Length: 161
Ligand SMILES: [Ca+2]
Ligand SMILES: [Ca+2]
Image 1 (tube, rainbow, N blue to C red):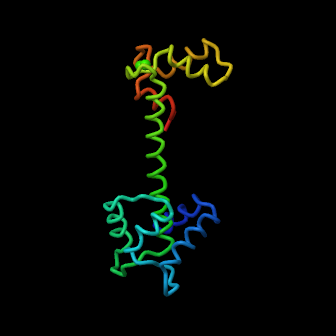
Image 2: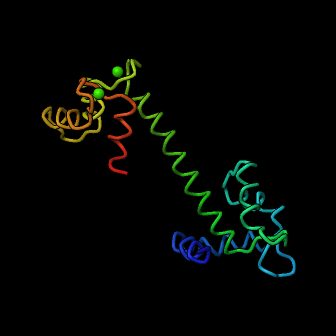
Image 3: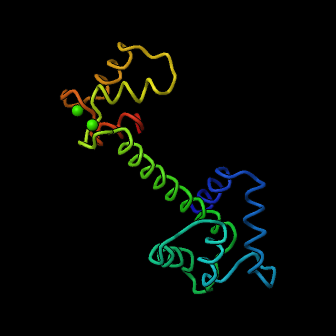
């Protein structure tokens, strides 16, 4: 069901981006065979802005090099590329979210209180009323303590996963 994975890897990407990826890829494919040595996988990934740990690179080669060819074809390469891209993106957002919280928690007590919540909303310039701010608090405040912890904040920001 790799061919399934392969088809889903291509659908995630736009054709121009896929061709750009190939253009980089083809730089390490001499014989014009459509595959590179798994030795160059990390390199190509990195030039195209992915940052796989050595351990994840080792897992991938392991997955693709089941026959001992010592090579990975462009299709299994887009598959690995999308896995990496998703793994990386998610990661970025976790971090920005963390930053966000630290910024919103103006007294750094570990919670966003109704006063802090109001000030940040009101600063958007949006025409939100008190009733509106207190509605978002109740809805997000899961243990009914009147404040939002990091835990409720993630739930708040990311909705229903
Ligand atoms: Ca606070
Ligand atoms: Ca709470």
